[PDB]
Amino acid sequence: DSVTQTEGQVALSEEDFLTIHCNYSASGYPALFWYVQYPGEGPQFLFRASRDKEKGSSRGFEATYNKEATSFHLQKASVQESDSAVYYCALSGGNNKLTFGAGTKLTIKP
Amino acid sequence: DSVTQTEGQVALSEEDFLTIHCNYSASGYPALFWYVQYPGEGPQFLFRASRDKEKGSSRGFEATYNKEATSFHLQKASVQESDSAVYYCALSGGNNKLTFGAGTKLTIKP
Image 1: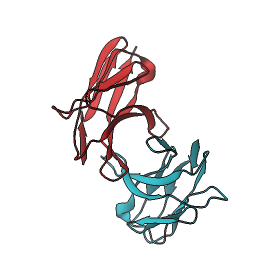
Image 2: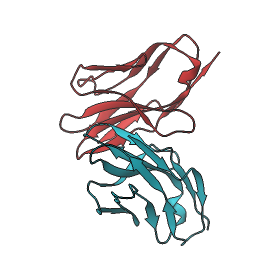
Image 3: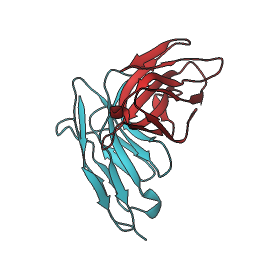
């Protein structure tokens, strides 16, 4: 199983629209996640989508489980300073362990 | 539910013995884990331990589930240069969600 997301960095300004890409490959019917990792901490659970077409969301963030395109893109209509962090796209299936992507460094500026 | 590990960086030289502490606190019987995040990559599953006294291992690393002291200390008898990475201690209660420690930077020397 594998996760591939927008690598590197994405630098936005406050009030901007955020879109982070994530496509995956897993057999079965995996759960899909989004975790946040603020500076000086470990990854923390953002939201989960368990079914195809289910849209997870938390803190203004959301992602729709799309199985035809095998993707789980993250969006936020208006990003703000305190969102500066690294976002990882993840999946749980296969055999009970979490598969993480490389993470995208989202840097917001005022 | 919380996980707390060896704050920061731990520097060593090849073949040394390592121990990165992890002390958890959660209700019920949680599954404990350690993940490794190699440079340029996302966090990855290292091993898990579901019940007291159980001992996980992979790549010469091992942690003993200690229900009484509520600890899950990572140990490797002889550390190697390829081992330089950040190690997280995780916890999963009733399936699904994983709670992460902040991580510890392990820096080996040749």
